[PDB]
Image (tube, coloured by chain):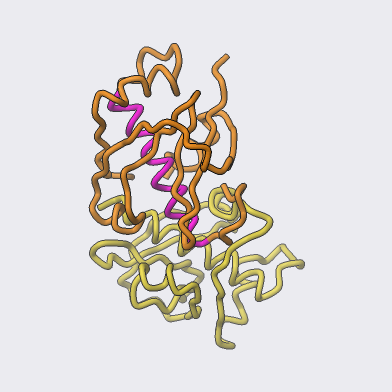
Chain colours: A yellow, B orange
Amino acid sequence: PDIELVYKNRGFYKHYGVRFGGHIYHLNSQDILSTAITGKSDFIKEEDDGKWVHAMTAPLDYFTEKYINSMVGSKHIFSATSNCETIARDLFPGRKEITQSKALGIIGVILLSASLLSLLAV
Amino acid sequence: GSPDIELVYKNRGFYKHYGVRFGGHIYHLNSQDILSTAITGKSDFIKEEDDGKWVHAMTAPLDYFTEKYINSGSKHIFSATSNCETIARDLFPGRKEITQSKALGIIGVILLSASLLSLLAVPWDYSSL
């Protein structure tokens, strides 16, 4: 099953999330600039409030090929509370090898990457 | 067939400032800070003689870079002086349909995108594209 990227407009950028069923997985971030420099983010799993905008639905491998272009990976440190312990099964169902830590890293870099590039859409 | 494009960079610590190396010169953006540049939404191109301090990132066909970075709405405006009037012939040889404006737009989005995404990369990973 595909990944659905969604966003909320935050004026000078878009804040992205992954919609799965009735929830959105996204980062607790006051703003992308601060987040990018500080190098750490906490994940939230929140009920869909109906105010997210559809961005794109595509296979996970479309997004990982585009943004996870390194078997070395990110400097960014991702954490999550236990309500995110569904993320591996939800977003990587077929993939037994994906631990929660790996899942957060992959999804987190996708969301941060999308948010950073949204700076160019003015 | 056309030569591959050589992406190079200078490390700025928190991110990498990328350029395209062709012969003895580097095409890159006049930018003190990548996030500042992205917010401003406009930048000027520079063509500079290679000072020997650029780091090799990746050599690849143009369409490797365009598939990765142009296949995802930039409204950034790229300008150049006549010092960049070689950019189309240098980086898009024998493609008459690539005007100067188009060449700046394509190379600009690649450099801005690579630079922005390097904010998330470990800073020593040269091949982080």
Q: Position of residue A55 (x, y in %)?
A: 39, 56
The image quadrant where one finds the N terminus of chain B is top right
Question: Magenta region: which residues?
Answer: B100-120
Q: Position of residue B74 (x, y in %)?
A: 32, 45
Q: Residue at the right extreme?
A: A97
Viewer-side residue, A105 vs A5: A105
In the drawing, does residue B87 fall left or right of residue A39? left
In the drawing, does residue B128 fall left or right of residue A95? left
The answer to if A86 sits in the magenta stretch is no
Q: Position of residue B79 (x, y in %)?
A: 24, 35
Q: Position of residue B38 (x, y in %)?
A: 31, 53
Query: For the point 32% across and 67% down, which residue is it?
Result: A8
Which quarter of the figure has residue B124? bottom right
Query: For the point 32% across and 26% down, which residue is it?
Result: B84
The answer to if B101 sits in the magenta stretch is yes
Magenta span main SS: helix
Query: For the point 53% across and 68% down, which residue is it?
Result: A108
